[PDB]
Image: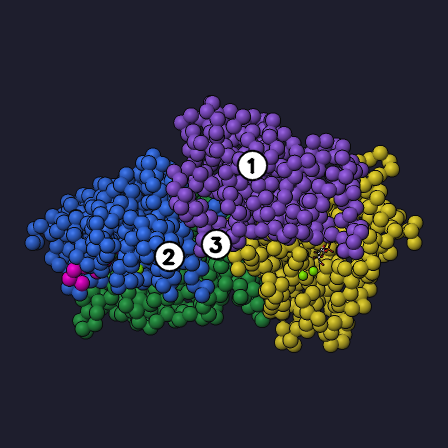
Chain colours: A blue, B green, C yellow, D purple
Amino acid sequence: MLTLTRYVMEKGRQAKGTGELTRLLNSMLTAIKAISSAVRKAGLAKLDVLSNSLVINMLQSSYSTCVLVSEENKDAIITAKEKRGKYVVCFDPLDGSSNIDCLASIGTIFAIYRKTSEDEPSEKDALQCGRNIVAAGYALYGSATLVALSTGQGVDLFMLDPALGEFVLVEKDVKIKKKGKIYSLNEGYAKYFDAATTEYVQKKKFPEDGSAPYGARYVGSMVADVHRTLVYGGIFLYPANQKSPKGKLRLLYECNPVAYIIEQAGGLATTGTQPVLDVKPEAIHQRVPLILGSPEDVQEYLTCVQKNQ
Amino acid sequence: MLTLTRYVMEKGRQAKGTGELTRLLNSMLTAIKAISSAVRKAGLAKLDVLSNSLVINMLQSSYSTCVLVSEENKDAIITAKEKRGKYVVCFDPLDGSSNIDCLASIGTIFAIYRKTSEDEPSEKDALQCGRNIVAAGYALYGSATLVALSTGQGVDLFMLDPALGEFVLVEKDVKIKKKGKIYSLNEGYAKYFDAATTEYVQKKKFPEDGSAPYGARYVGSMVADVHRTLVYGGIFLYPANQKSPKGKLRLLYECNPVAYIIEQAGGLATTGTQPVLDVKPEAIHQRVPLILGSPEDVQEYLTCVQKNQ
Amino acid sequence: MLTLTRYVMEKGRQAKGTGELTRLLNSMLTAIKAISSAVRKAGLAKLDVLSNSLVINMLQSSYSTCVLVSEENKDAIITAKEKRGKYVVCFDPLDGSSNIDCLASIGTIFAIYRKTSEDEPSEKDALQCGRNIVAAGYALYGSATLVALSTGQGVDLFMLDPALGEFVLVEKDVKIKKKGKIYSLNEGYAKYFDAATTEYVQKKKFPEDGSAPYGARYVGSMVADVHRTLVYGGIFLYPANQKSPKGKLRLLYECNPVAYIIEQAGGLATTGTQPVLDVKPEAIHQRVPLILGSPEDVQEYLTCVQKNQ
Amino acid sequence: MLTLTRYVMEKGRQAKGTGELTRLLNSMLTAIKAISSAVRKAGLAKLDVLSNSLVINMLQSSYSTCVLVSEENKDAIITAKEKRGKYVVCFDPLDGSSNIDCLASIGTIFAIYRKTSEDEPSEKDALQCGRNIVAAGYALYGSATLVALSTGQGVDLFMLDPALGEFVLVEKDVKIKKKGKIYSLNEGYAKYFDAATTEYVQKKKFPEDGSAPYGARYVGSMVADVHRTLVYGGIFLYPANQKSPKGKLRLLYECNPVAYIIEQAGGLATTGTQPVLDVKPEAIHQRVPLILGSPEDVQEYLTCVQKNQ
Ligand SMILES: O=P(O)(O)OC[C@H]1O[C@](O)(CO)[C@@H](O)[C@@H]1O
Ligand SMILES: O=P(O)(O)OC[C@H]1O[C@](O)(CO)[C@@H](O)[C@@H]1O
Ligand SMILES: O=P(O)(O)OC[C@H]1O[C@](O)(CO)[C@@H](O)[C@@H]1O
Ligand SMILES: O=P(O)(O)OC[C@H]1O[C@](O)(CO)[C@@H](O)[C@@H]1O
Ligand SMILES: [Cl-]
Ligand SMILES: [Cl-]
Ligand SMILES: [Mg+2]
Ligand SMILES: [Mg+2]
Ligand SMILES: [Mg+2]
Ligand SMILES: [Mg+2]
Ligand SMILES: [Mg+2]
Ligand SMILES: [Mg+2]
Ligand SMILES: [Mg+2]
Ligand SMILES: [Mg+2]
């Protein structure tokens, strides 16, 4: 039984670390477990508020953090001097608000950076390119609870063993298919799509090479849809549209973490004009377009962008 | 704490029943709990086979059944003479095979009939119109575990309390909105749709009255998509198409139960030409088209069918 | 998987009952499960008050009761006319107060009678001899959670399956050994014992026939000590002493239920002068001496009583 | 929520450790959780064998150990060179065999030492006086699951939060009463006691100063009885007797750990002639007499030893 806590401590032993990142991850994972439990019994009772407190408190108490960015907080949270550590965490404590009442899969998203500037800790420490991620992942609260995690050496999948109360490694170093057979976007925005998105979607439904149309899936929780894309392959799209000209999804704590996971699994994640991880953030709640998945599907989307530009 | 077992026994006390239906439901619910538990720890290990055995064994042992129809069994299962009861159960022991690996919501579906013929128990006892349902419902194994149940007096929702190990009533007599704002179908089959489906879908994305386009959602597990339709309103479609000319979804143990639930909640469920519950089944594994949800959305779909016929 | 709910409903099907006792037992068992859960997480927070409310509410709501006697209530609780059923329940909702802080096994004890008088329901309906018990048992909240139950056809043991959230039959028709090798009493009261108890205890430690002395065990929760006596054999004693001249243990909701269980398993349960189940109660909180266990050990205790009288 | 994993990592951050002890404790605690779960569902199925494997595998995999002593293994287990760490663990993976069938509290016991010799790792590294313990504690699998732990700075109590799946600090720096009112030993061995034990026990039942006799408690699992002694005060005795002239309890992995806990809480733990922690072990499965608890009660026992020597 390779537990996440035993896996992470072991990974930190081979790298001769001080144990600070390990302490941070353990704290994050503890918050995730409390969130999983609250989610499993939610209807028997706001959850946004609770999951946000849980994450902030656990992270700050780890003595590993200097700056936190949460979806739930207008401004960056600076860690009190007495608990100052070297890491910056951007997180979405509970994503998939739209699906809570209807019991669909929802999740938690996070990315961890090392503070590199010499200055006093500020929001600017949270404005690194995703290419500078130290660790990132997500939890999926679905038919079972799962964490996808990467620290730069590929993507590992862990599942909450409910009897044992701990995360157990179920898949090591997962790789996305080069090409899938599923496309995933909200086609309710079709009226507002750019020409590139329209053309790409048309190619999926009416291919010109005799292949079967792709199947469509859209849970409407990003973590569920991205996780499906990871394990089954294909493409997930939340592009710019007329109602959301800069996209809807948030760069720091939605797009960068999933982009990091998808790239680590051998996939691609793009704004349409450049890799998501290469976008230099200008503000903590900045939005970007997100198109991600199997490299050949994303590469085909990029061709549509290129001939329509 | 109004538990499902206490709710069902109480419902049977006011109706002066022998307790046979109550015994049947309790058995079904016990199978559901075992399924929930196996689902929650699935990745840590086929599940179709297991959930099928669980349901068959629990139902047969209730002394309440004479005939069972399962998705997993070519032929109807006749209950051994010594355990013969008066009820017929059609069930899908685990639905949403496509979503198991990716951890999306999956479910169990069932409908219960009283055997009305005088003959020896046979498959023909399972070929009643859904309009003759005595009890029907589904379990949803999602971020939490839920059962929707009706015995003819509206739809009640129950949630598995994990600490207590029992189903607890969370919503009594639920009603679907008259009109929703979500449409749900696999648009990957667009190339194969009939004119009516094409036109309806076009109206959702490009309305002609100045209203916002509907949002699209499609989990790709029927129970998840139908449950969302129930609680948020809107429309779910699995119509006939060129690849599935009679539809894909199964009449006895997929469509009739959800149709029964949706109608009990004040919604509509149609094949496109008639109510699902009014279809006289000719074979236990018969397929039908399924269009269901908020009455005004379904009524609008039926208008598209009518002007394209 | 023979669950308690399926076992009890089945037992009621063969006996052509109205289902009223079955509804009562299910309710009692639901309270037991809630108690088990509260007990498992007690230190992470009175419990007497909670467990009492749980039992009273569940029993009254079953529409099966007319009179309740609780250890926690000075007077008998008469069921409101609208929920009147035919049964009387005497219960100790949580026994083993002394062991809660130190985490030793604790339990719940109950006996069920049919009201036989024609009069208005009163405390007098709870003053039947234990010989008139319809059903009785206990729950043990120990290293695992167990229920011992009898309805007149021997003793069955059930264990809470934590994954499944239900009681499962683990042993059918259990029989106590004719003679054991363990004696169980608080020897701290030795100064206050009568001559009979003194002599019996001396015989256990200094036998005159060359046999090994009995081992001593005393958890100090009656349910734990009685359950051990049931499965390992031997003798449990809470006799009269100078500080408690009529004994300490309560007749209605401590002694009668365990006496009923022990007798059903082929054991004996005595006051020292007569079987516990044959004592005609005069008051709802009456105390009796309790000596119970393997028939040959109890029979040997009775010989000490006889030669010292 | 101060979790054990967060508490232990934090305790290791202030002490600038390499994290090796922390990794060891986490591993031990993970084994404890698996044991708790197996114990909670034991009757629904040897456990000695399982719990032994769990502990050995978890400890060896921590890269923190060089030598293990288990009750279940004749010889010391030398850690393979590739996983060699600096610590020695003596453990009883599951104690209280006698109480498993009857569902009474049972436990796991452990003591951790730093290897101090320069030689190749051998059994001799496990023969340090308990006074050289680095960390020690026990788990109690009772009505709830608890760990008592000390690393030299007093005794902390943790409880398994079943919803959260982790140990949570419930009491910091616990102190035993100076004098209690409970004595705990198997009085079935009275025929075989030495004069000192006889006299001490007589004083508890027949005091000569007008005080009330002590109450007697004896669960017959050492961990349960010792834990009760810790939280309620009093005295626990397993002295030498004619059948067990050197005592029964094992020095390395039963007596030293509980002695360490009791001393850290301000109590005393003696063989009758010297502190348990000061005994120099000569063999890994050596037995000693054990008398422990509130200092004034133990001090009174020692006076009986002294006037009978
Ligand atoms: O309804 P829409 O516009 O498709 O938005 C759904 C998206 O919004 C989110 O809830 C976060 O903004 C994602 O989880 C999901 O992908
Ligand atoms: O991939 P498709 O064709 O959309 O099929 C999905 C449907 O199939 C099912 O798995 C059952 O056939 C449903 O749960 C779901 O609605
Ligand atoms: O401390 P004593 O006098 O031995 O009393 C213990 C007895 O009291 C009870 O807590 C109930 O009165 C029983 O569970 C137990 O047998
Ligand atoms: O039956 P006895 O001799 O009192 O032995 C009980 C003791 O044995 C053990 O099981 C371990 O030897 C302890 O847990 C307990 O204190
Ligand atoms: Cl989902
Ligand atoms: Cl106990
Ligand atoms: Mg969010
Ligand atoms: Mg979000
Ligand atoms: Mg199926
Ligand atoms: Mg199906
Ligand atoms: Mg009580
Ligand atoms: Mg009591
Ligand atoms: Mg042992
Ligand atoms: Mg032992």
> Total of numbered circles in the picture?
3
Residue in the image at 68% along x and 69% along y: C73
Does residue C272 appear to the left or right of D156 in the view shown?
right
Q: Position of residue C211 (x, y in %)?
A: 82, 35
Identified by mark 3, the residue type is: Ala
Asked whether the residues under marks 1 and 3 belong to the same chain, the reply is yes
Does residue C219 appear to the left or right of B138 in the view shown?
right
Ligand 12 sits in quadrant? bottom right
For marks 2 and 1, give the one nearer the viewer: 1
Numbered tag placed on residue A57 in the rendering: 2
**Residue bearing mark 3:** D163
Stretch in magenta: A244-253
Mark 2 crowd level (few <14, some 14–19, many ≥20, 10 Å Cα): some
Residue in the image at 21% along x and 52% along y: A119
Callout 1: SS: helix
Residue placed most toward the observer, B134 or C302: C302
**Residue bearing mark 1:** D131
Numbered tag placed on residue A185 in the rendering: none
Q: Position of residue C219 (x, y in %)?
A: 69, 49
For marks 3 and 2, give the one nearer the viewer: 2
Identified by mark 1, the residue type is: Arg
- Residue C53 visible? The answer is yes
Callout 2: SS: helix
Magenta residue check for A246: yes
Chain ID, mark 3:
D
